[PDB]
Image (cartoon, rainbow, N blue to C red; front, side):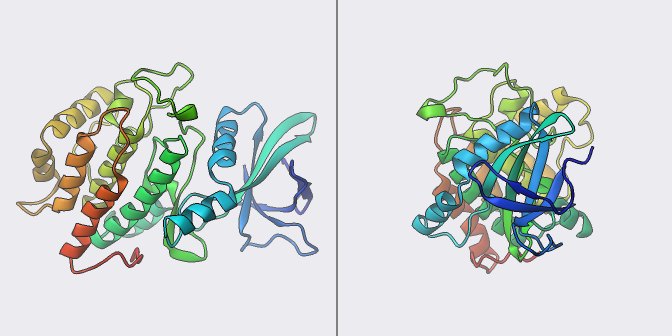
Length: 316
């Protein structure tokens, strides 16, 4: 079922016109023109059945949090170079072959980080890991301040800007969670209308305990990615078919972070900014607002330690 005739012009709810291209159900897209949509198209159009739950969830997040001017204004005020939240360009409803579809136009990207990680024999340098994590912290602060948590940070959800390999973006908000609607934090409890536990090797202890994801969970997920990226491994990676095992290790390692460091890093040679990062996340209550700038400054010490600085170079 081809949802679009290639090269057709579609108009979104605000009457903005777009041309649809070849796929990369996501298709290359661009502004309406006499010219065809090329391989170097700046946008993609995602189309799903109108009854698809995740697309609606993702679209609401994009409308609410990723308006182009909204993002630019944040970038300018917080004095960032960029912000890795993809931009929302429009959406609508598309009926084809007697069925109803929903579509959304968003930024197009280059490679995901997982392909790059694997091509590098599953290692990122300390430099690369710290630079990635600083920008992810910028992203998490932004979405958290707009009432959402992601719940599933990982390399395959991190894409490079297709025209700038030093900018990384966090994608996939189909199972993102609105933890703070109208400024009222969700209680420490399960959400019946939510099925997802994240990705098993990276997910939060909260998620393992069947509680809705919150801000501390996102920072914890990022913690586990940092270790994975630095070392090629997590301690519980042998037994991911048993979520009981994975939660148990996580809980015990949270209780003793030095033993996590000893386990994951050689000898007596563990990067202290990572330990400090995890110690800081461990102190967070379920409903508590992280001190994002403190977390960034902890990472900045890692860079100072290795003879570098936050120069924006991901060094991939």
